Length: 128
Image (cartoon, rainbow, N blue to C red; front, side, top):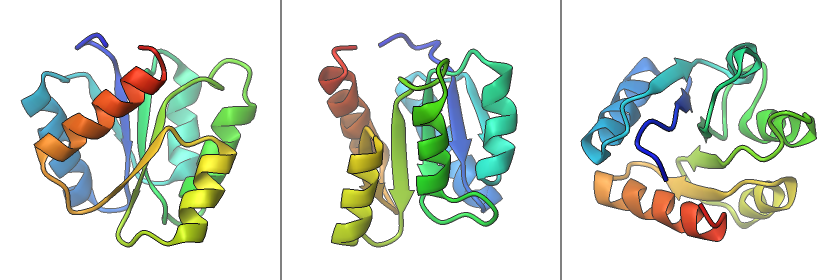
């Protein structure tokens, strides 16, 4: 994995998006773009060039599982790594996500060492 890999940070709170963007930067990942919901996110993904999507399970209009499914079915973007972000892990959320295609899942709040570890685990699983 390449430091110029372009991220899409999707979250309903601007503060949460600022926090993730800070953590990516601290890791050497500076090409980050943000979205506020699932729908907003497809709008930009559509533009192309994205490399990884980091998204919130619960967002209005188009949620985490809904956005992921949309990624997975689209010819172009179907392979994009998708990290799911949630406040509380539930077994069935984790299954739904895994089964629909999520590359990983992280419970928030998290530190940079923890995000680094999730990135490293997806990058190795993906043989990236």
